[PDB]
Image (cartoon, rainbow, N blue to C red):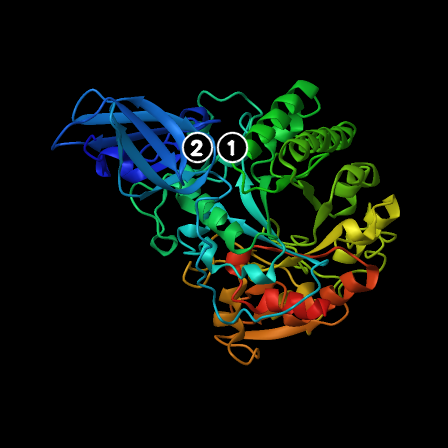
Amino acid sequence: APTAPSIDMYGSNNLQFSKIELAMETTSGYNDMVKYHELAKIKVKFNQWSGTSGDTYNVYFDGVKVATGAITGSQTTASFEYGQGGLYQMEIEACDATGCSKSAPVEITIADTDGSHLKPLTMNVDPNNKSYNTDPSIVMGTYFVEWGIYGRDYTVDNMPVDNLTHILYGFIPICGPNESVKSVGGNSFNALQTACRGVNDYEVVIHDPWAAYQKSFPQAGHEYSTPIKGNYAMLMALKQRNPDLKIIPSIGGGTLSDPFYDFVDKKNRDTFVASVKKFLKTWKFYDGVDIDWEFPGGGGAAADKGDPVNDGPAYIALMRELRVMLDELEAETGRTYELTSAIGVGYDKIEDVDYADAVQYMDYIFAMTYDFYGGWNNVPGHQTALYCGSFMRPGQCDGGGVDENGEPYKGPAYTADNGIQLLLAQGVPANKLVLGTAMYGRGWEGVTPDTLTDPNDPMTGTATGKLKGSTAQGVWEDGVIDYKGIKSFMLGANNTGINGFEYGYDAQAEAPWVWNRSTGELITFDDHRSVLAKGNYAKSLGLAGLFSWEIDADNGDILNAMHEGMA
């Protein structure tokens, strides 16, 4: 008998292997960084120092032979391939003409992007998130942002996953024209430039490879030789804990929507749809695709883009073509894939798309019932109100009147109700519409009493500019503040108002605000009361459920109020 082999762990990459090859210590083009292989490459070194070595070796996973080769010395490197992810007990035997000698069993890791090699994720959720057993048929969605791991310090394990049915991962960019990303500043455009080097235009890529799969998270138990790290590995482990939880990549978003405007050319859609298929086969924890085109017809971040005649038909064509693609994946894997989309709900946004047509190919429409008003101008209003507010002029709500200048309104007011009603009027089934909840405030400064036409309602005032504040207060961008920040620094424990702020609620609109009279700071958001009204509203009309944006900005209260509202 030959000497029984002993596995060189550190010379065999600590027995950590993967079906997906990921660059861990660099930042380059997408095709250069991530290669998915049908068969994982296995390379194990074993030693036989004393005695005889034999002439042939055999490799066993869980007792089944998976490889064979030749031994020619006291050191042998066994290179072979295996196309199944998971954890296996490995034994290598050495053989001569008289017999074989098995090595001691040792656990080999073969990683795959479904997380079949991963234990369920250990949760670190804020206890303020309460337990609810809401009907499983109702959708409870949220957006988890890739960049939330940095300043916001919010990670996958922080999410209250038992209170969620859908998790939309934002955002997956598209290579090509992206001048809207540039004017945001920071590193976003640079990171996108890098990711798109050696990548065809109109293909999807990972924006932040560090956040996605590189960063070691100690809470997830990420070691040095771990083949998949970052948010993606944590989401893979999350699916092991919550197998029925839907995790869907959100493509586009506000600033990353520029390439969508070239989807009127079908070859650009073909390229996109195929890359999305490749992305889904590469990252198997994903359960579909969320399209966030902002907006068909224009009126978004790209001031020079938008085709009100062609974008709508292109959007519909895209949804059909994505469905066909997802049906292929459903056939190949035996899985259910979902097609969703987040959409603007203002009259002018909806009029450019026949959604009744588009929605036949889709599972859900995430009605972006927020951002009605904001810091982009000095006109106060409710950013995420259900109904028309007290501040509005006669004939503004339905759009049949005139403004203070005298010019007629071109359509109904920016409210949640108006958005939902216009979609139902088109022929969109209620059970496919998901109502949106804001986990953030939009703010102004300079809305002082002397600017109000109604002394009791600050929404009848005039601002000087965007709200300004620190990241410690939850202000990450001008005119935008986390809900958790509003609670801690504007509302206080009793919801009466602190630090010069006063709480107010428009009962007609179902919309709250906090207001500092001296600084003129005014913040419009969603609170417990307004989310209860939205929960009731969605239940009243038989909507699919509720979704939120964004999860990191919540302290628990908003999602709690979402479940309480649907009860």
Q: Nearer the viewer, residue 474 or 107?
A: 107
Quadrant occupied by the C terminus: bottom right
Label disc, if present, on residue 97 of the rendered structure? none
Q: Nearer the viewer, residue 225 or 316?
A: 225
Sequence order check, earlier mark of 2 and 1: 2
Q: Residue at x 67, y 35 (%)?
A: 330
Q: Residue at x 86, y 53 (%)?
A: 401
Q: Residue at x 66, y 40 (%)?
A: 337
Give the amino acid type for the residue marked by disc 2 in the picture: Ile
Count the marks: how many? Answer: 2
Q: Camera-side residue: 113 or 442?
A: 113
Please rate how many residues cluster around mark 1, counting C-alpha atoms within 10 Å: few if below 14, some from 14 to 19, many from 20: many
Please name whichever residue, 103 or 227, is drawn nearer the observer in this view of the structure: 103
Q: In the picture shown, does residue 488 fall above or below 213?
A: below
Image coordinates for residue 542, horizontal then vertical, percent? 81, 59
Would you say residue 185 is visible in this rendering? yes
Indicate the quadrant where residue 304 lies. Answer: top right
Residue at the spot 28% in from the left edge and 33% down from the top edge: 93
Q: Secondary structure at mark 1?
A: helix
Relative image position of residue 289 (x, y in whole percent):
63, 39
Compared with 231, 256 (above or below) is above
Q: CA distance from mark 2 to mark 1?
A: 8 Å
Q: Amino acid at mark 1?
A: Thr
Q: Which residue is mark 1?
A: 282
* Contact, mark 2 vs mark 1 (Cβ under 8 Å): yes
Residue 142: image x %, image y %? Answer: 60, 54
Q: Dot 2, how many residues are within 10 Å of its Cα: few (below 14), some (14-19), or many (20+)?
A: many
x and y percentages locating residue 280 in the rendered image: 57, 34
Residue found at the far front of this picture = 98
The answer to whether 111 is drawn above or below residue 95 in the figure is below
Please name the residue that numbered disc 2 is placed on.
20
Q: Secondary structure at mark 2?
A: strand
